[PDB]
Image (tube, rainbow, N blue to C red; front, top):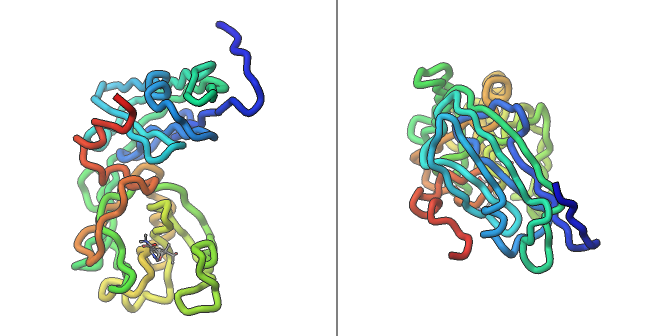
Length: 268
Ligand SMILES: *C(=O)[C@@H]([C@@H]1N=C(C(=O)O)[C@@H](S[C@@H]2CN[C@@H](C(=O)N(C)C)C2)[C@@H]1C)[C@@H](C)O
């Protein structure tokens, strides 16, 4: 143990996800987010030791200047134990910025839970370890505001949340603007896509797309999703008229092809 002297305005703290001791889904990447921009990505990666059991090949990819992710080529095998040692204390992270402390977390992978939202059938089907446990009618984004296709990682969940168009730069008082109370909302993208309760589209669920891009389901089905789907589980959207979710979204990691992810984006 060696003390690292510091100087105000030249320290950055790492924050690691998922939580210590947590059980997460098969899509959960290791995430290390710093409270400052990181100039020397190579130094940061060198200081982070991720080990797995059973062992699988994984690699780092930076979503932006603040946050690096680590994942394998394919979804985790259930039961896998993951250990994360962020040994950044005193590490020069570039441009006079030094790691403020170390962090050490461990987590495990739970059941394989993959929910497929098929735009052609307008059914969201939840499969746990391969078996269908739930089929829910859904209404996705209308043609002018479609839901993006791709693999989404399940994030946070809310019993209630406010959808306010003003955080998207759109005044509430201008159709395309809105201030919506929503129950049972499960986040699937940082950009703001959720699976949530939508009593106002129950007639369209299973039939037509009427949403702004979110996956509208019934109140009971949304609560079910809130109760039974956890961080790191997967929602795959297929067959919409939209494009693909950006790989750097925050929950879109799996949309980046393995060869690109593995090659990384730290200087050679
Ligand atoms: C759920 O319906 C939310 C709604 N869904 C989306 C989405 O699917 O992207 C956004 S709509 C916004 C309009 N312009 C789009 C854009 O800038 N890009 C890059 C695709 C997104 C919004 C969060 C909300 C109504 O709860």
